[PDB]
Length: 394
Ligand SMILES: O=C1Nc2ccccc2[C@]12CCNC2
Ligand SMILES: [Zn+2]
Image 1: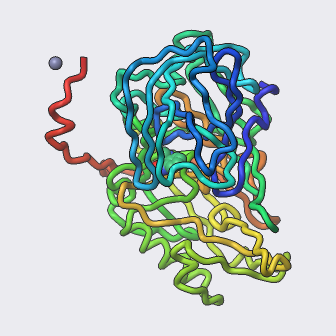
Image 2: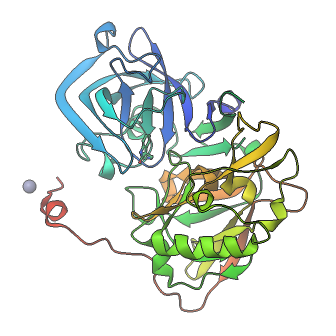
């Protein structure tokens, strides 16, 4: 899988992208690797934040589906026109696929200035594809049309006038053993829509938050490479910040820091890492009543940002933030670990990443099993709206 190592790039906090080609002749574009969505969509007209964009008219293999599409998120939205074309990943498997492509004609707060990506590769399942689940996602087409095994794995590696460059690997169709150390532990995919998982316990420096475990998964928990932060439901976020504040309390930061709105700095090389606690998320195991924990360091949840003003200092942003749409294990979580999206066996694997940032006292960890007697169900059941209920699924 050596051709696929180091096939991701980006700027810290602005997303990890893979180079792709679309059309004949091939048009090169940088595409955000997003496990939190299910569309393949590309800028297809001019925009202040785009260096370039997909030109449908210039591809001999383009076919128009004569259907539009709209995709809104909490943060960002876009629209455009559906088609199919030939798609390749130059630093990926040596194959070409005909895939659905949404050509983005208008957007708001979607593209990011300086991020260097021009589209989004949604790697999650058909159930959350827009406009509906009959629009086959890219990965589904790749698997149906070629020999590629139904699995991919991600190694996201964390980091004065520009943000820090980041790198990573998307291994399509298998697992590369150079990218991790130790044991690979799996948590079941609860339902194939998002990459939904179940968190059963949360500890901050070995201390249990002691919430009803449904709170951890209210209203869902997902793994999303296209989200920067670890995002936590309001109640959990408040409890967690209260605990990190207590552990770190020899230092008094502004409110803005804990809201993710302000940097805090120390003299170059003097950051007191050991005043900030590790955070452990216990995930449901493949075996009933078992779990395993993934443990991240402050080196994951404190994001480095060079201050043009005091570029003499090491400065950081707090990258845990509040959610009202459940837990999101974003790049903060993922940068600890080699993460295996084992779609074939409806599971997600975690192992300690060979590239994760740590120090000489602590490492990110993946440890199990931990066993419980008579587990409560920690899953939440989203209220069924009449809209969603009325959908037929043929
Ligand atoms: O919710 C989001 N808003 C946004 C904006 C731009 C790119 C990617 C995204 C996501 C889509 C799913 N993962 C993150
Ligand atoms: Zn019907």
